[PDB]
Amino acid sequence: SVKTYMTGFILSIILTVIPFWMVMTGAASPAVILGTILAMAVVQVLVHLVCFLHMNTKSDEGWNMTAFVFTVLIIAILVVGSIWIMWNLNYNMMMH
Amino acid sequence: SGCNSALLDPKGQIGLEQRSLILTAFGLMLIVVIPAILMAVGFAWKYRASNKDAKYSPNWSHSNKVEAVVWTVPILIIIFLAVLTWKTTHALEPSKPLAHDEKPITIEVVSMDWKWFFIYPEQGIATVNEIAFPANTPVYFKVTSNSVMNSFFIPRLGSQIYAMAGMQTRLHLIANEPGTYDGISASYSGPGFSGMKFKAIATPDRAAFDQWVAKAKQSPNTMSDMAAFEKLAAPSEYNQVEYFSNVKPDLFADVINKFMA
Amino acid sequence: GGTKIFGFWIYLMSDCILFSILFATYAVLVNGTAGGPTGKDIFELPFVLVETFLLLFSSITYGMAAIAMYKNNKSQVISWLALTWLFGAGFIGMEIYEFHHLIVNGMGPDRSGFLSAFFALVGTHGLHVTSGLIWMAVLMVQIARRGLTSTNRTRIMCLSLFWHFLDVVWICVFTVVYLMGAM
Amino acid sequence: KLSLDAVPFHEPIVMVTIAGIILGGLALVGLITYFGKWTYLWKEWLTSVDHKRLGIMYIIVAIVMLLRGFADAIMMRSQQALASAGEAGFLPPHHYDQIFTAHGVIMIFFVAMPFVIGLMNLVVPLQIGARDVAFPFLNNLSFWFTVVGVILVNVSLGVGEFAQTGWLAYPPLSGIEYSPGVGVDYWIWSLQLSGIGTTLTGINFFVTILKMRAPGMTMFKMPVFTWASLCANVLIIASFPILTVTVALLTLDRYLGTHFFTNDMGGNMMMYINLIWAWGHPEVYILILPVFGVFSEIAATFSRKRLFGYTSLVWATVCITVLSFIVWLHHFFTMGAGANVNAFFGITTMIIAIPTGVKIFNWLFTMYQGRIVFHSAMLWTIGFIVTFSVGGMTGVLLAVPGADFVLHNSLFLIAHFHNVIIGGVVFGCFAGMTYWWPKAFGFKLNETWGKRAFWFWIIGFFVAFMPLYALGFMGMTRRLSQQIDPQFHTMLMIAASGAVLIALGILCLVIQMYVSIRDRDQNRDLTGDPWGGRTLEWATSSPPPFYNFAVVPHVHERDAFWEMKEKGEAYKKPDHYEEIHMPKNSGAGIVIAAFSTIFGFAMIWHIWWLAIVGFAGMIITWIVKSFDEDVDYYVPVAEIEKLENQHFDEITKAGLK
Ligand code: HEO
Ligand SMILES: CCCCCCCC/C=C/CCCCCCCC(=O)OC[C@H](COP(=O)(O)OCCN)OC(=O)CCCCCCC/C=C/CCCCCCCC
Ligand SMILES: CCCCCCCC/C=C\CCCCCCCC(=O)O[C@H](COC(=O)CCCCCCC/C=C/CCCCCCCC)COP(=O)(O)OCCN
Ligand code: HEM
Ligand SMILES: [Cu+2]
């Protein structure tokens, strides 16, 4: 597994350097910088999942990608419900 | 379920719509829950272990016919209840301007430490554990807390809102009938929580509310300056009704800005 | 044998839930700067960058350690584990150094809600990395004493999941708390 | 440096009588252990890595803490009955506010979670044909973390206080500025340890169900209590970490002076309610799903009929598992949120009622055309259907935001959650006790006192919380202790009478536990398969062997044991018994928990030196236990022959095969 870790080494470096460069040096309107750092972070997370964690469909008869998919769904539900609720809450708590 | 209770037979339009919603939701689930209990007892008696003439048929698991109605009838009742819920949640929400042809009276509420403070900015009055509003006149509550979360709640008028420090919550109420309505904090706040009771004297007319304001303007003490507020915000469990002649022009905002900063 | 790896994987899913809760708390409290730092003026992005490929290199050297564990060599696994522990200790030291230049100043976790949530999220990631460093040290001691025989290579495969999950959490961390705070 | 502990525990009050009673009972139990079995308790219990004994100890802790929780609840009912239309009661506001908080915390985390976890621990490894849980030492450690939580919430009674904020400790009142006492520290440091233990329990059982199944038992061939436990463990894994965070986020609020939830310097208190209920409702379904499995098994067993809707009853459980994370805002509808979020979460709450209703109707149709024998467990099942249907109906009445705006924290909410919690979890945890008592302990509970306990419980509950629905409709709010109202007196006195009836029910249950143990020999389960029995837990002996299986049966069908009873191949002398490795009992769970008790009590009271050596006591033992290499022992085939032949001696004595 030397190749896959080194494949996930140059990819990890090149997807953890361009976000820092885009943010520190600007060179892009805020909306493109945010979208690109978020995309590069989702892709680097997937690269670390597939290359480093050795994620695969079969695993021990599923239940690893399935468990990870369920955990991602619950994380998304919890985060988007703790932002959407609190955005609607904090909006309705103002002098306005 | 008391017939002459506060939830049943409310004295507010936002409470009457709330009771209608409660009754129709309770009715919608009777046609499901009541069959459930009735079959729970009927199957137990009819089949039993000694009722040997019953159709004792084991190993009968799957029934596409039975499971179909079992899934569908709650689905239909919940779809209808969900349409009703959406309508009544966008209709009976607090901060809804209550769609009336009268000018809402703004009553800035501040749930202090085991007492309620009310500030009528337009009238200049300030009261402790007592409000008053004309009959069939909208009342607009800027409910905030001073120490800990509370819940402004007039059960007969319907609907409650949460009082949080640094946060202004909007609560529109209205009293369709004149009279005195009990008020309470519905969120536990401390040892004096059982004493956070106020009265809501829904005056018969605007003239009786002007009489109530004029009586409050005869209070020798006045709500001038924020330093008085800290004196009133001192922890005390059971506070008698106290009136204040005039208030600082923006006292409720300065209560919120103690925390919001 | 393989049940322990699966159990640790679902514990890592539980830690994913924990870190998601911390991320939501930060994302809501990020604007709660009570007349203090706004985050943009204190995050010092280059200091994060040297941190972020100081924990990125750590995952790669632990990967080397794991692929050596697939082989029978023990010296290679101990050397790569020591390198991983050095990189993790450097990361934790940089975390403390950043904190020691925030708590000494009037910039501590009690300064504001935003600083409290940033300190909680990053300190919880740092406490997970420190738990990983203690676990890596204990595992190195076990490997030296007993070798990659059994229930020691299982611990290698659970600490690999732990360390790589930690680096993924730090990917999310530098993406969200850092970086986005400073534009 | 004793730091904040000092001399004042509770001397000027009459909780020192309760403390002295507890000390006397502890001394009596210590003496009874002293003469008789004292190392046995250490060597077979208290160190066990066996799922059956850990489950029994979980259930014993649940009963022992149910006595204290119900003592708190009878004091609450007496205080509320006295205060209404009368003078002040025996509980001042200070003390009473520790009574509802401790009642809710003890009943939820130490009476319901341990009871459900004990039932799952005892049954699931048996049902899935597994010799033990996947992580036999993460089970004893988790039990002892539940025990350290119990010890902290009981020490709170004598030393210090146990929080005057509510059973969830809402942020501004539970903050260090408004609750400077150690009560919220007791709450935090008991709940966090209990949550760690419960998260480890959930991990253990999730791996056990997914990986330790018998060969041939697929996902849709498992018993329905196993599916329900799998769903509750999914929820435990995906929800208790939230409880770990927010409580910890409260801890830093009270210890480091942070501002996560303080309303002063940018903190948002509304975040704590969002997180605590995003954990809370998933924990509610964690409590209710295993007893749904318990009632599915009891109905299928005591109706002598196959479970009606297995596929529907498994997919409804899975839908409840996945839909319980989108509902939580229905706990703070009155927070002031917009109509859109309130309507969305109310609709989600009403959509999470279709699966439960489907499960109820599946159980009803399981009774349909069946030989319903009215055992105590079946009576509990019928009472559960009757009460839980009402409790859920009132639950969906509070699920419409337009009605929760006016019924949020009334006694109608108290009646909803008490109706569902009792007629659900409590009925399921007593029906499991009656149903699986032969399968853990060789005797059977006395059916005469079991029926009396059920009738007392059902009648008392229906006259202790039906009045609370009327009180909620009358405008009474939750935690009223002093000067309630004259109007509330009649219904509060009826509720007090109902609480007395529930006390008589608990006493009848205690008498059943005594009259059965006294008659442990004048009844018995020689076969190992009493009351028919369709799942793969009744194929063993009534006190099942420590390995609990010598063949790991093939199953290859849904019911499994009912199939092999039907087609004869039920009781077959297997023949060659291979050596099977069983985990070795380790006491490292006790010390790690004990330092936790040292860590918790030294964190509640600010003895940092003892907390440093308490937290470092947990770690070093964890390190030392890692070094341990003797973690399993092979049981000799001679003992497997001796036990299995003994079991078949009784199978043969009766009908046999
Ligand atoms: C484990 C116990 C348990 C269970 C199973 C439930 C189940 C439910 N609960 Fe409850 N709850 C429980 C325990 C609690 N609840 C709470 C709080 C709570 C609140 C808080 C509101 C507020 O805070 O102001 C709401 C709205 C509900 C609603 C519901 C609903 C809709 C269900 C549904 O899942 C019930 C589903 C069952 C039904 C519906 C009956 C069977 C169905 C049939 C017969 C047919 C179905 C079809 C239709 C109904 C159309 N609950 C609280 C905390 C109170 C507090 O301190 O704030 C607790 C402890
Ligand atoms: C005085 C010390 C002060 C330290 C301060 C900094 C915090 C340090 C925290 C350290 C926590 C413990 C780290 C792990 C030590 C033990 C490692 C270990 O045992 O490894 C092997 C172990 C068991 O392997 P088996 O083969 O099953 O063993 C069989 C025999 N029992 O492997 C495992 O799978 C265990 C994995 C452990 C993961 C630990 C994760 C810790 C997470 C911490 C979260 C913190 C959250 C933030 C709040 C912190 C408190 C304010
Ligand atoms: C300071 C803040 C408050 C918290 C204080 C307490 C902190 C945590 C203390 C330690 C708790 C965890 C102890 C774990 C003990 C070992 C677990 C273990 O290895 O169990 C094995 C299984 O191996 C595993 O690794 C289990 C599966 C994977 C579990 C991974 C998570 C373990 C717990 C990590 C810590 C969780 C809490 C961290 C802190 C959270 C925030 C407070 C059991 O199976 P056997 O075959 O019997 O093993 C041989 C026994 N001689
Ligand atoms: C069966 C006997 C029980 C009785 C008589 C009883 C009675 C009560 C009473 C009187 C209250 C206070 C109501 C109020 O003033 O707001 C209460 C609160 C509560 N009970 Fe129970 N209860 C019982 C069992 C249980 C069980 C089994 C659970 C859950 C496992 C439970 C959980 C709670 C909770 C969570 C609260 C609210 C705590 C709080 O507000 O902080 N109770 N109970
Ligand atoms: Cu809920």
Image (tube, coloured by chain):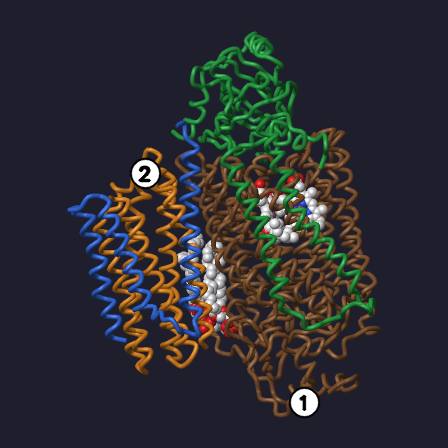
Chain colours: A blue, B green, C orange, D brown
Tell me which residue sits at (43%, 23%) in the image: B253
Ligand 2 contact, mark 2 (Cβ < 8 Å):
no
**Quarter containing the C terminus of chain B:** top left
SS type, badge 1: loop
Locate residue D38, reporting x and y percent.
69, 70
Circle 2 residue: C106
Task: Name the amino acid type tagged 1.
Answer: Lys
Locate residue B130, reporting x and y percent.
60, 20
Tell me which residue sits at (38%, 72%) in the image: C157
Ligand 3 contact, mark 1 (Cβ < 8 Å):
no
Neighbour tally class for label 2: few under 14, some 14-19, many 20 plus, Cα within 10 Å: few
In this rendering, does residue D103 appear at all?
A: no
Report the front residue among B180 and C99. B180
SS type, badge 2: loop
Locate residue D524, reporting x and y percent.
79, 75
**Which chain does the numbered disc 2 sit on?**
C
Q: Which mark is residue D612?
A: none
Task: Name the amino acid type tagged 2.
Answer: Gly
Locate residue D327, reporting x and y percent.
51, 49
**Which chain does the numbered disc 1 sit on?**
D
Report the front residue among B33 and B163. B33
Neighbour tally class for label 1: few under 14, some 14-19, many 20 plus, Cα within 10 Å: few
From this viewpoint, which residue is outermost toward the bottom?
D576
Q: Is residue D612 left or right of residue C104?
A: right
Report the front residue among D138 and A21. A21
Using the image, determine if residue D255 lies above or below residue B165: below
Q: Quadrant of residue A71?
A: bottom left
**Quarter containing the N terminus of chain B:** top right
In this rendering, does residue D533 appear at all?
A: yes
Circle 1 residue: D573
Q: How many marks?
A: 2
